[PDB]
Image (tube, rainbow, N blue to C red; front, side, top):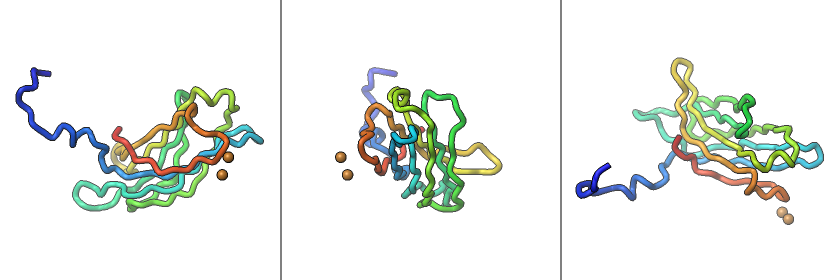
Length: 143
Ligand SMILES: [Cu+2]
Ligand SMILES: [Cu+2]
């Protein structure tokens, strides 16, 4: 925006991953039935509301670039450490899965306003190890 002579910072700190919580999920391709199984297990350390209070988290799960309706977990009210314990199934033949990307996005449910996103992350199908169940914690990223 300018020569950048004045500024200080701060800039390195602003680049770091924000503490927006983490989501544990699992993933397995069922070659018998030809479907992708996704386990939305639990989230931890979701951020407290600006001025105290807990959020009402739920997770949207879907595949890009597919235009189909997103799956959603139940809403867990007033908790920053929800255990979802839900499984979703995507009926997609393996051959068609390679170019897709799984997205998991945690939102804060509200009945009277747009639901604020808490954070999200993506899992490209082309870097998943289909020979073993995948299970990991992922830090939620801004957006
Ligand atoms: Cu093995
Ligand atoms: Cu093993």
